[PDB]
Amino acid sequence: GQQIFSQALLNANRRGEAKTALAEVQARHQELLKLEKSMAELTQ
Amino acid sequence: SRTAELQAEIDDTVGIMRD
């Protein structure tokens, strides 16, 4: 005669140590503006 | 590695076409 709940711990703390996903997310942005500038030059 | 290759290809087309 007993019941219990449970609480999760989210972990995935390798990502969580940083903001969350910055491996191919923030770097992609970094190099994608570079693509934009080079294409601007190519079209110019 | 795809994005770097695309950047390189764009740079090369830029070079050809500056010429």
Image (spheres, coloured by chain):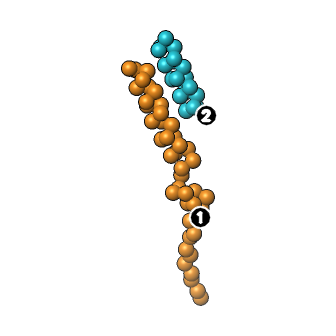
Q: Colour of chain A?
A: orange
Which residue is at 54% across, 52% downward? A21
Residue lying at the far bottom in this picture: please name it.
Answer: A1
Q: Secondary structure at mark 2?
A: loop
The answer to whether A20 appears left or right of A37 in the picture is right
Which residue is at 56% across, 70% downward? A8
Q: Secondary structure at mark 1?
A: loop
Q: Amino acid at mark 1?
A: Asn
Residue lying at the far top in this picture: please name it.
Answer: B19
Looking at the image, which is closer to me, A25 or A38? Answer: A38
The crowd level at tag 2 (other Cα within 10 Å; few <14, some 14-19, many 20+) is few
* Horizontal and vertical percent position of residue A32: 48, 36
Residue lying at the far left in this picture: please name it.
Answer: A44
Residue lying at the far front in this picture: please name it.
Answer: B19
* Horizontal and vertical percent position of residue A15: 57, 56
Q: Which residue is mark 1?
A: A11
Q: Which quarter of the rendering shows the C terminus of chain A?
A: top left
- Mark 2–mark 1 distance (CA, rounded to whole Å): 29 Å
Q: Which residue is mark 2?
A: B1
Disc 1: host chain: A
Q: Which chain is cyan?
A: B
Q: Which quarter of the rendering shows the N terminus of chain A?
A: bottom right
